[PDB]
Image (cartoon, rainbow over all chains, first blue to last red; front, side, top):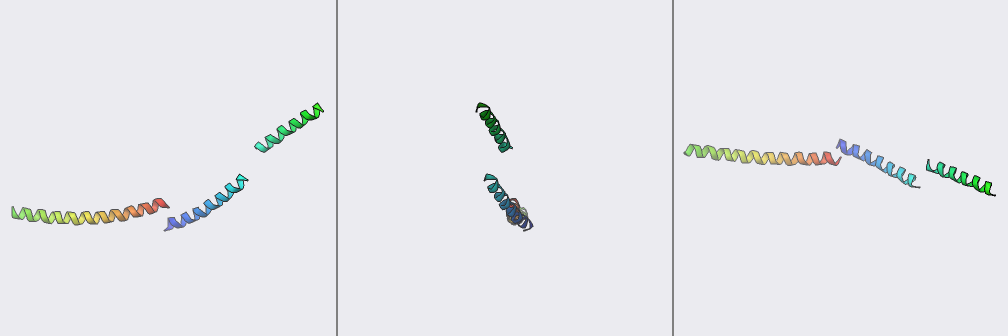
Length: 47
Length: 39
C-alpha cells in the first residue's frame, strides 16, 4: 500500500514527464542559424 | 505392520495438511510479490 502511494506519486511524475515530452516535441538551431548567416554572407558577396 | 500402516497414514495426512497450508501461504506470498512487483 505504501508502494502504491509511491507509485501514484510516480504516476504524477510520469504525467509531468509526458507534459515535458509534449512541450519538447513542439544546439542544432544555433548551428542552422550560423549556416544561414554564412549563406547570407555568401549571397551578399555574390551581390 | 498395523502400527506402521497407521503411523504412515497419520504422517501422510499431516503431510497433506502441511502441503495445503504451504500452498496457501505460497499463494499469499506470490500475490504479495506480484503486488510489490506492480509497484
